[PDB]
Image 1 (cartoon, rainbow over the protein chains, first blue to last red):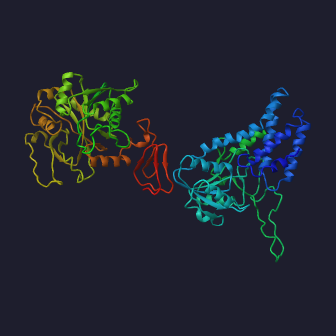
Image 2: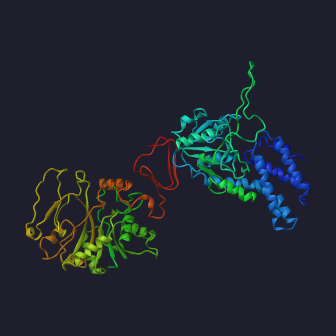
Image 3: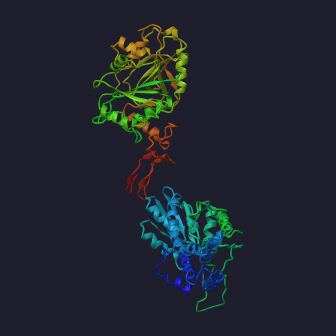
Length: 302
Length: 333
């Protein structure tokens, strides 16, 4: 029936259906066909489909995290030894209810996380997450004064994409390069970030230059922010500064070339430690330091 | 010591404010986006008043309707407001005789002319009034005074010179002077009847008037007896001192903290700038007294209420206050 193909169908869609929430909705559809009455036939085939999904993954982390929460909810269903049928109907229904919860959470955060941006504050924003930009838009809806500084992130050129999406709103902007990002931290009140994942330790899984931002801000004593939707938690503990799950290059040094083809190769995803984050924002209240681990301990019961 | 009644002199300094007071009353006007009466009423509540009196005649209907809407018509209030309706525009002496004819004054009563905002605790004042009343029987009224801004060279409307005792703090003389605005008069003549009774004479012009009074039951009886007295400061105080009834005393109270009565436009402007600054430590916009107020303090003395709307790239200054539901455009200072 396929799950990778269902995820590939979301091309011109996105924005509303968040990348993990669309993968979770795809997991529920695959579950509801071949009877969730059996726990040997279904769960094993769900595990095989997640393994097939991980094997097809090039540079995504959040899809593995979202699977875990689904699994957890499924197991928790019939924890009351309830009827093998009303528990099943509640499990199938919690697929569309899971996607509907992404809207309700965004409604919560955009009213909570506008408080952090005070009267007339210049912001240097890095990365693009649907939660952080929704704060930025619904603060403009709240009629609050804020300036914006764009970071030239280099994955699939994200800075230019961010700049254009800020133009459509009506907020004054200018391009700042990630090389010169050190020379900006004096005319900037606060530094904001959108994460691809949040660590078990309390650190962050992010883009092509975020640790560098974290350290410079720690030097300048200027605050460093992480805002996300509460589903990007993996049981992952990157022990060192340069160790992450990869399908491509972990720093490759190429031979002598004349035509110039083999060059680009650098760490596209980088980790930053727990100390560098001043504040973290999700729908699960306002919490930063040891909070992430407590969430993971509560979920995994281990 | 408990049970205290207060009388407020409104309809008193009208047309002293020249372009205004045409349609709406004197005391309705806001200092910091809130009526002048509200400040006075807050001073009454902090003092400990159980019964409130107000004097309304000109634009009296608008005053009465404002009291109806006020936070004191509601049963939980420590004081109840009763309005005195008199003939249109009369002197303070005429109102004093009217109130004595009605006869509500019991023991020690309060009289305030104009609207005064002060941070000075009144509990100390009452005690020192009572301590001095126990000193001798024939003792009348209490007057408040505060230290001026070093030199009163900009203060021309209030040129009141006070002669005071170092030991008993009794007032001797009151005098008005045209001096810096109109260079015509220089001379001040003083009565030499009280020379060796006092000995420690202290003459000062460096004191601000307050016109806030703690008064005994003697006062309304004296006003009816001597109906020639129209004023309460210029003729009355001087008349009391200059052997009208022998052995009668009046108080003068010195206080280091801020207490300024509103009277003129340029005095009002200074008081307002003092309120925007942190001169009146308790009396600040952020505390919110009118209940509808939602002001919040920001650094560099900038006040903003809730629902403040402002355009981007706009500069705000020092000692500023902006109300609720307010919109501002670009390029504003």
